[PDB]
Image: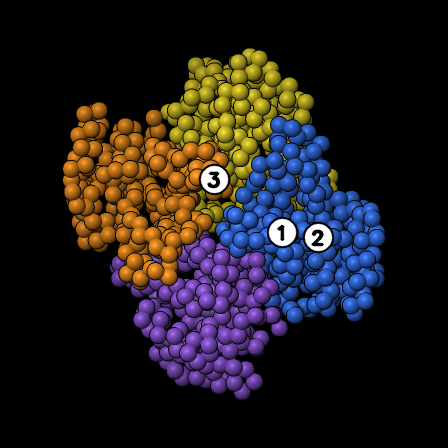
Chain colours: A yellow, B orange, C blue, D purple
């Protein structure tokens, strides 16, 4: 049970995986979670039903996070349904791994546009909708790959390393109005394990609880920071 | 609040300030706190009575965290009282700020011995006692000065930067036994404020709750990490 | 001064500023420099004349480093002319500083496409043309803003932090063929003071000579590194 | 053929390994190198003779870099012989690897005092002797282990991570007098594990030495407080 002064959170790309776990974790901690899905609603709706059947507060919302007007419109609808938006998690993202010499600029842009510009739009709009209340916390879901790089991931590492640095700039622009911006860098989340000191993959739950901490009031003096969740894979 | 599988914690140098706060916070979330002091029990005893009067579990203990035998014997004593030790916070440290051309070697060793060797002994003995249980979390209280350095603090920055790197090595050695080692780097904790994006000093409680998270089950995939708690002063 | 096994280098956006200085420095060390410019040829031509009359080897080449086909064909031309290309410096980049709430997606993309995708293309083509000879060095001109962020520069910090992470992934992909990839992070440079420890802006030649070292044989065990050239402004 | 405004350099623990290559490299670029050694004069004196026979300027000096009074006396002897001291390389260092539960505080201190306290003394005395000239550059030889830690190296990682942070503090203190302080973090240097190194080989001592030379040289005049990785890609 983590303490939250805000009441609601938008999680982009939250139908499955880490984003889904973020939704369950934050819902179970008493926040109303907005589950963003791009295309099919069946998985998102099921996650929503699961949480409500547990007595939690959840809703789904359709928009492409890579789309400026779509994302903008959605935030407005959430401010119009709940009165505001206190928390944002930029989780949406894709991979298209290729050795760089086989990588077209279209493949580079596919990952940049979906992973970095999406988080720009989200952080920008959060700044607009939380500046009024002088309260908000935003978490950007980056990756160990943005910190250290990886074979075959020149485009993914660019998107996540640009995310990490973008977040710092947003932290300066939100700081006087008490809007915090931070990043999480998960390692390998469920041989790969041979290089992990904890000798196991991380659980999606373990990422989700690190996000919860950075959104929560307990991290109220943490901004512009990158929280590693990698089991020791990178120190 | 935060969930803890373990039951007790030892905090070095915990009579006041950040150390006292860590003791308060961890006591309020159900842990038995051992409040370490090395010379005068007064303030530490007031802390104990305060926490007990609020309904928490607390105890004082006298040893010099810079003495190997003192630290070792105190941890043995706590293991005898409680059956073991789940959590350790290496918080004890001193300053002796001087421009380096005025700094004697004894002024360098003063800070190293009180600040870095203390945390080596604590980290070492935590490994011994937590290894049996195959469970533990250890937080080293470092400082922004150990990340970026500072005019007049060649000795303190060496002690805290050494603390950060040491803790990474202990994280490797504790990992298979599920014993985690992390560092917190506080910034300016209650002209200087102008350089802080959040435009205020940090509260001691805001450091303590970051320490709480790193000890908690919620950070279960985080080891060898340094967590910045500095209001954006360093990114 | 410094020793180079390679014979030539392409420098993007080399008409003025740091990029011009890079050409001057590298030309004076015996390399044939290829001075890239986008529109105005006069300044680029004037630089070639200067370098040529001083007794060095220099050529200009027009193309938009943000344009995939332009960039690909230019490197093709240089390989046609010189037989190869041993060195690449991705220096081209633009700024469009705005507070994020004033920033259109179009403004974010303007900087991403011109700063990040341009460097991706150059790095990718370097991999292709350098791999046969199993030799080369590539330097990416990033920025302190990519390391610590800056208010009003969510887009520039994104592109340069993305550049930094990118470069590391290229270092993995080039490593086995001895193709090195490193970044330089300049501070405040005169052509581009209280908080700067050296108490002055950096000269463009001071950036150029750090780039030269990373291209040189002297840095032959250095790859995936980011070299800070900021007068102590960031440590 | 890097450019140096200064004329001489002291390299602690320079009789072999990386420190010896630093002396070779820097002597071949025209500096008078002072080769520090602790006990064995034979290898240092062979090195000195090797360099002099190639036309370079070299000298040996015996002292313990971990002894404040020795280190202090040695630098006044160099100032006495040469008129000043432009450059300093804190290379002296040892290892005593043990799992932490088997390591006594005295094994911790042995590494702290030999690796970290020595670099403090050297940096401090550099500040003193370089101040009046308002010119100077100092390189601290740290390690990848100080950046990321290592199993069995809680003492070594502490000394070298402390050296890296401490060097940044010296950079602030020397900056207005234009005395630069920088660190190098070599990876695995010759004199399996090679699988994790992207460049697929151990580094040559010469490759560390030339990185050191660059940070000493005029080419790095706007670089201070920096840590230069020299690890073949092992840590990025």
| Left or right of A94 on screen, residue A231 | left
Query: Residue C8 is drawn in which quadrant?
Result: bottom right
Image mark for residue B195: 3
Residue C197 at x, y = what percent? 50, 53
Q: Tell me if I can see residue A97 in this picture.
A: no
Find residue C189 and name its label.
1
Percent x, y for residue A187? 50, 42
Q: Check the image and report above or below for A113 versus D5.
A: above
Q: Residue at x 70, y 33 (%)?
A: C107
At x 36%, y 46%, the residue is B142
Could you say whether the residue bearing mark 3 is in a helix, strand or loop? helix
Density class for disc 3 (Cα within 10 Å; few <14, some 14-19, many ≥20) is few
User: Can see residue A144?
Assistant: yes
Secondary structure type for disc 2: helix
Residue found at the very far front of the displayed protein: D132
The answer to whether residue A172 is left or right of residue B107 is right
Q: Position of residue A23 (x, y in %)?
A: 49, 24
Answer whether labels 1 and 2 touch (C-beta < 8 Å): yes
Q: Residue furthest top?
A: A81
Mark 1: secondary structure: loop
Q: Residue A53: which disc?
A: none
Q: Which residue is mark 2?
A: C17
Q: CA distance from mark 2 to mark 3?
A: 30 Å
- Rendering quarter of residue D69: bottom left
Q: Chain of mark 3?
A: B
Mark 1 vs 2, N-terminal side: 2
């Amino acid at each position: 049970s983590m303490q939250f002064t805000g009441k609601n959170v938008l999680i982009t790309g939250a139908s499955k995986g880490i984003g889904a776990e973020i939704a369950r974790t934050l819902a179970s901690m008493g926040l109303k979670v907005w589950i963003n899905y791009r295309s099919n609603a069946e998985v998102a709706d099921a996650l929503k039903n699961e949480l409500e059947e547990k007595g939690y507060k959840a809703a789904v919302i359709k928009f492409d996070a890579a789309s400026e007007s779509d994302f903008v419109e959605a935030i407005q609808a959430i401010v119009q349904s709940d009165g505001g938006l206190s928390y944002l998690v930029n989780n949406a993202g894709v991979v298209r791994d290729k050795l760089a010499i086989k990588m077209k600029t279209e493949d580079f842009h596919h990952v940049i546009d979906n992973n970095l510009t999406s988080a720009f739009i989200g952080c920008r709009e959060a700044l607009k909708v939380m500046s009024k209340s002088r309260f908000g916390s935003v978490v950007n879901i980056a990756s160990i790959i943005g910190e250290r790089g990886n074979m075959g991931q020149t485009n993914y590492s660019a998107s996540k390393g640009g995310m990490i640095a973008m977040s710092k700039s947003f932290a300066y622009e939100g700081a006087l109005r008490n809007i915090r911006f931070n990043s999480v860098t998960p390692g390998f989340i469920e041989d790969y394990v041979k290089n992990i000191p904890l000798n196991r993959l991380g659980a999606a739950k373990e990422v989700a609880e690190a996000v919860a901490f950075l959104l929560s009031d307990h991290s109220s003096y943490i901004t512009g920071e990158t929280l590693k969740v990698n089991g020791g894979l990178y120190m």
